Image (cartoon, helix red, strand yellow):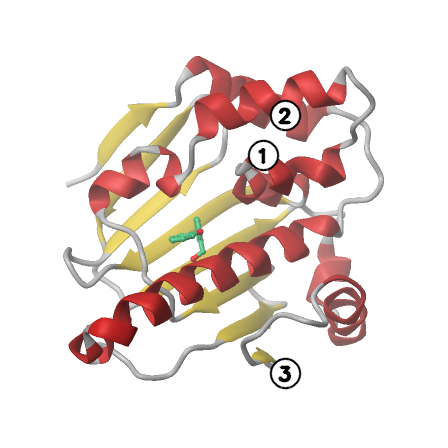
């Protein structure tokens, strides 16, 4: 049972700008996704301060980076608050309509694409490097769902049949054929050290083979 949705016109416009604009500094996608994961981990931490049972779905608060050269995927996993089905459909918990508006007024006033995260739509920087993005998520108040989009104006949502997650979000980047440098251990390490060195949660870079 797969539901197919149209992006709001402004989000489709943001996504086409990210895909079609010539912009070499693509590596900031990882900073933006790690920052999103950190924000989601902050939220479940804050909720657990007054209700410890919110961590019954998992006490550990962390971020994992999993490259897979055979599948040509880079997966960013966190054990944050996760997203309900409603949040997934509503632009993955973002204020994407007003954020895109603010972002594009900034771009014509001297900003560049690397500043996307200041406008709440940093998730969509995934399409700097990915031809398709899958988002698997589990929130304490909902079931496990899979969101997917290859851009082109539509996304799908289905109940996830895969591995149970407990709580949190998994962003699977199906990389473009010429963006496989982001599967290389030394390149990911360099980017994490450059842009994410002060994130307040353990970031574990998995190795392969
Ligand atoms: O988990 C990071 C993440 C992944 C995909 C889309 C948005 C995300 O950012 C969140 C999600 C939920 C709460 C707060 C921030």
Residue count near mark 3 (Cα–Cα under 10 Å), binned few <14, some 14–19, many ≥20: few
- Identify the residue position indicated by label 2 in the image: 103
Residue 119: give its label.
1
Residue nearer the viewer, 137 or 102: 102
For residue 113, what is the image quadrant?
Answer: top right
Q: CA distance from mark 3 to mark 2?
A: 36 Å
**Residue 166 can be seen in this image:** no
Q: Secondary structure at mark 3?
A: loop
Q: Are marks 2 and 1 in contact (CB under 8 Å)?
A: yes
Coordinates of residue 176 in the picture (x, y in percent):
66, 45
- 209 sits left or right of 123 in the view: right
Residue pictured at 49% horizontal, 35% vertical: 150
Label 1 crowd (10 A; few <14 / some 14-19 / many >=20)? some
Q: Position of residue 166 (x, y in %)?
A: 25, 73
What residue is disc 3 on?
Answer: 207
Q: Earlier in the sequence, mark 3 or mark 2?
A: 2
């Amino acid at each position: 049972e797969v539901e197919t949705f149209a992006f709001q016109a402004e989000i489709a416009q943001l996504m086409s700008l990210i895909i079609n604009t010539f912009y070499s500094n693509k590596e900031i996608f990882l900073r933006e996704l790690i920052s999103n994961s950190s924000d989601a981990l902050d939220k479940i931490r804050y909720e657990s301060l007054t209700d410890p049972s919110k961590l019954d779905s998992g006490k550990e608060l962390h971020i994992n980076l999993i490259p897979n050269k055979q599948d040509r995927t880079l997966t960013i996993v966190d054990t944050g608050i996760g997203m309900t089905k409603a949040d997934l459909i509503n632009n993955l918990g973002t204020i994407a309509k007003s954020g895109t508006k603010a972002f594009m007024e900034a771009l014509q006033a001297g900003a560049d694409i690397s500043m996307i995260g200041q406008f709440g739509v940093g998730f969509y920087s995934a399409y700097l490097v990915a031809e398709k993005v899958t988002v698997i998520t589990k929130h304490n108040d909902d079931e496990q769902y899979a969101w997917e989009s290859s851009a082109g104006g539509s996304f799908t949502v289905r109940t996830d049949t895969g591995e149970p997650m407990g709580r949190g979000t998994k962003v699977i980047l199906h990389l473009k054929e010429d963006q496989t440098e982001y599967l290389e251990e030394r390149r990911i390490k360099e980017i994490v050290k450059k842009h994410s060195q002060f994130i307040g949660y353990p970031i574990t870079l998995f190795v392969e083979k």
